[PDB]
Length: 354
Image (cartoon, rainbow, N blue to C red):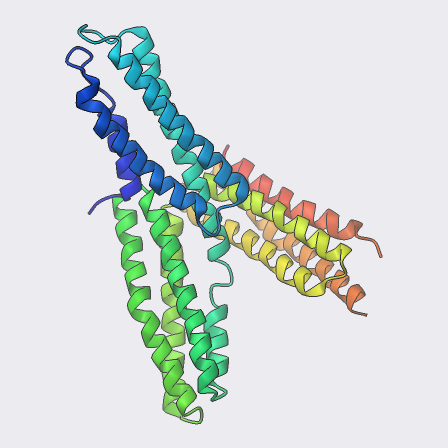
């Protein structure tokens, strides 16, 4: 029950700005209208200051917050004229359209800022567990304690992002489906920690081991449920555009790493590029299930398979060449392959948006 709090606030605000021109007074409406909008702006600002929001995006959100605020001022001015007449006159009408457009624009950047998080956060979603299990398999209860904390933080970050996606969603069932999933991640987290702790206490115990395995398997499952639910309330539009932005950022980083002969950074960053690619194909395959087979799904799936079958492996191989040469030359091959990954993602997006 309920949609996202921020979504609902924005939706109400769009309704509440529509007033009988005749019975209007600033004294009566200004305070609540102003308050609603500022409350929206606090939410948008939190979002904008949040860890994964890119700089450009924080800037655009900030610019949209100043623009709605000034749009309401403009609207209220126009209501103040136009007072004591029956019909909304022209300056008031266009002012209402303006208020509503800017509120749409704000929504868009918020959706985009939420993708920044989704893009980053739902990569290599397993690593922390794997690390925490390796430590447990070693005995060191000091070390298992700290990696357990790292696992908790990652657990919460996932739930944090789920929540962010909820609060801008207008899909009541979708939102419900993610909150449940996030709940399961909450109860499941400490239990996974226990199994790890009990295991590290007695690393030779076959029970402790089987028990870790049962929690490993459950957790990985439930993360996939949370991932999918979040995917399900996220527009593939925003997913594509943000994945394109991030891939281009990652490419720049690789290029730098290459300039610096830096294999660690190159390897970690090219990994993200592959993850992000895998995640578009994931989300887009899933989206195509909402369409009957035909011309539209055909073009999309041919573009998804080409990226999958040909272009990615050709990118991974090229990375290996570089890492081999730097570990022991022409960068053209790495540039060309990165461009083809990006471009492959553009073709998917073109086909989806047909």
